[PDB]
Amino acid sequence: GAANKSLSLLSTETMSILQDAPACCLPLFKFIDIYEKKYGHKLNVSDLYKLTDTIAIREQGNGRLVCLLPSNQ
Amino acid sequence: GAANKSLSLLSTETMSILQDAPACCLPLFKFIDIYEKKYGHKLNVSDLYKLTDTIAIREQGNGRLVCLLPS
């Protein structure tokens, strides 16, 4: 599972960004910007929705919030 | 159980809305408007992401698209 391997590494990179954020969450636009600058390549946002053991993505009126699940903080 | 039946109904409602849309696809803002008008309550957009056998939600630059899979 090349895909599973890439998703697993992405989960660690997600953890690394969000463990430094306040309340371990970030607006989606900001997460994308932080990620792409940090790793130097494009984030495929649909991959975040596969990481259901790592993060929840919450809808809000003005945009999504990417939230690190309590066990991963 | 209840969760599967709740998702199963959302699937049927989602298909009904998308069947005759262009390319069986609606921008998310438009799917929400049509859904809320048809069903008279708020759509649980996170539950749509659980319908991985019925729809794909496409990230695009101009906003999300809700797309019925081949079927």
Image (cartoon, coloured by chain):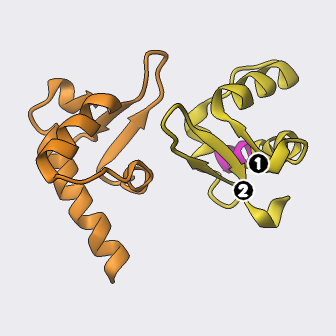
Chain colours: A yellow, B orange
Observer able to see residue B47: yes
| Mark 2 Cα shell of 10 Å, populated few (<14), some (14-19), many (≥20) | many
Question: Which chain does the numbered disc 1 sit on?
Answer: A
- Mark linked to residue B25: none
Earlier residue among tags 1 and 2: 1
Q: Considering only vertical position in the picture, is B34 above or below A7?
A: above
Residue at point 76% right, 48% down? Answer: A11
Above or below A37: residue B16: below
Give yes or no for contact between labels 1 and 2 (Cβ–Cβ under 8 Å). yes
In this view of the protein, which residue sits in the foreground, A37 or A8?
A37
Q: Which residue is mark 2?
A: A54
Say which residue appears at 40% left-offset and 56% top-offset. Answer: B47
Circle 1: residue type: Ser
Q: Position of residue B49 (x, y in %)?
A: 43, 50
Front-lying residue, B9 or B41: B41
> Bounds of the magenta span?
A2-7
Q: Main secondary structure of the magenta part?
A: helix
Q: Position of residue B7 (x, y in %)?
A: 31, 65
| Residue A4 drawn in magenta | yes
Report the residue that reaches farthest toward the bottom: B1
Q: Are marks 1 and 2 on the same chain?
A: yes
Q: Is residue B53 above or below residue B33?
A: below
Q: Secondary structure at mark 2?
A: loop
Q: Quadrant of residue A47?
A: top right
Pinpoint residue A48: horizontal percent, then vertical percent. 63, 43
Quadrant of the frame with the N terminus of chain B = bottom left
Give the distance between the C-alpha atoms of the residues marked 1 and 2, in whole angstroms: 6 Å
The residue wearing badge 1 is A11
Give whichever of A73, A53 is nearer the camera: A73
